[PDB]
Amino acid sequence: SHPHIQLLKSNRELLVTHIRNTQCLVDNLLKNDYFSAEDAEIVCACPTQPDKVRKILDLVQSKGEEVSEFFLYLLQQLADAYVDLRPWLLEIGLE
Amino acid sequence: SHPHIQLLKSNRELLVTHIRNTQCLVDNLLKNDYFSAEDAEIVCACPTQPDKVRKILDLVQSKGEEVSEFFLYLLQQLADAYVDLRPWLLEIGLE
């Protein structure tokens, strides 16, 4: 079976509505040779963040289980990277 | 005065210990023409994440108030980008 692909296909709405930045995702997929320039360009053509997430998920899924697993670990990494600053960033406090 | 520079210089330890990824930061500073290739290379030479954060802060600060403000808004943006996935990513559940 493909448990990581299934995770993406089964929780699409969560991902589509709750990823507010797709550039870090594309940049990392490019750097690690999972996305081509072509793939990034296709994602670029999608105007809105939700539309872009949909495209990214569609591409990742079609590339298969290993790319899907890599994507989920990337999300984990990114979600953890700056999370411990969240309290301070409210206190300072930015517009 | 330089309130955003002061914010970086006064909360260095928080930032140095609680930023776990510097690549998104460098990538965005490069894309927006605040960092040169030279600057990225200098950050690259720092082995550990804490060492890299120190270097990034030093460079941002020396570039001045507007770059410091941009940096703080970047941290805000990045901290918000995937934060709403944090509960799900525990549930699934990755290594």
Image: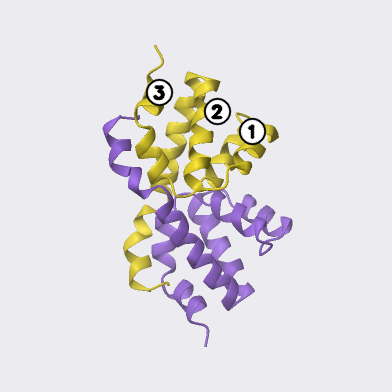
Chain colours: A purple, B yellow
Q: Residue at point 53% right, 56% down? A: A51
- Image-based side of B17 in relation to A73, left or right: left
Query: Quadrant of residue B35 in the image?
Result: top right
Residue at mark 2: chain: B
> With respect to residue A89, does B4 lie above or below?
above
Dot 2 surroundings within 10 Å: few (below 14), some, or many (20 or more)? some
Q: Secondary structure at mark 2?
A: helix
> With respect to residue A26, does A70 lie above or below?
below
> With respect to residue A1, does A38 lie above or below?
above
Quick one: label 3 or label 1, which is nearer the N terminus? 3
- Image-based side of B27 in relation to B13, left or right: right
Q: Secondary structure at mark 1?
A: helix
Residue tagged by mark 3?
Answer: B4
Residue tagged by mark 1?
Answer: B39
Picture coordinates of residue B82, whole percent (x, y): 41, 54
Q: CA distance from mark 2 to mark 3?
A: 14 Å
Residue tagged by mark 2?
Answer: B59
The answer to whether marks 2 and 3 mark residues whose Cβ atoms lie closer than 8 Å is: no
The answer to whether marks 1 and 2 mark residues whose Cβ atoms lie closer than 8 Å is: yes
